[PDB]
Length: 48
Length: 178
Length: 96
Length: 27
Image 1 (cartoon, rainbow over the protein chains, first blue to last red):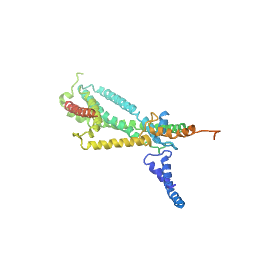
Image 2 (image 1 turned 90 degrees about the vertical axis):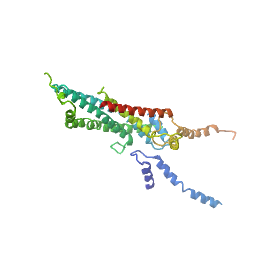
Image 3 (image 1 turned 180 degrees about the vertical axis):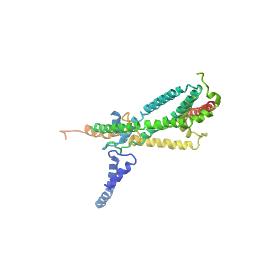
Image 4 (image 1 turned 45 degrees about the vertical axis):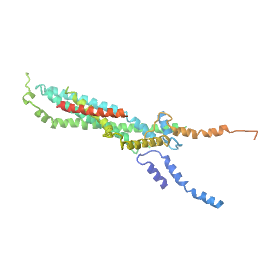
């Protein structure tokens, strides 16, 4: 929650008071799905 | 409505916008608060006209001496004209400042296209009212701090110097035959 | 004649104010423009890049509202009409 | 753009001359 609040507060950089920015969701999912890269490679290693 | 719809469909233009975007509101209000340049300049010129009429009206009673009412009017009116440029410049710059930030943490209250456009309009109208209030409270003050509360000080301070310094003192005060 | 002069002076001051900004980047001009060429190249490249990003990504600073206005939403109508070209073309029954 | 730029330059010089004339006439 703090991690995404900072994203809100950075992409609302100067302008103010508007609903919600979608690129906050964008950046957070891009940060969450970048660590899927380890389990998939581990499964490939297991299959090997 | 059509302009807002297109702004919504273009400012998150490549990807499905799951939140009502913001630069559209900014673009609409910025496109609407730039038509104020005409009424404010019209107000400034109208005030200039009445204030020159007042100077002529309150110099008419100086007809005791001719050739000095002419000088006095010719100096005060030239001062007012030399001040109209500055006051119009500041008038333009005030609204030009208003076109910069689009504050929304003021007392402004906090398909899918129709709902998005309705939400955008309910905010555009509010901010139009709140910028109208702020330009209505600062058009008088802007005019007078530059025009009136400065021509008054010109009258009370500098008029005497110009009148005494202009040449041919003997003819500046012509005794009228009357 | 002397009454009119203040108006002319202030109006021409406003016009010179309008032109002086353009004269700012035009203080000097030499043949073959050794550095103006590179500077203008950078300006054009930055304008093109920011306009591409504004046209497709949808950056800020006043995107036009006149038309459907650029590939971004045309590109979207492709990404969300292709799921109709998938449905339409493929079919068979009672031979399977 | 080249003709526009040169005509801007000439316009600026002409306006400078006009304001100099206003200065030397208003006196």
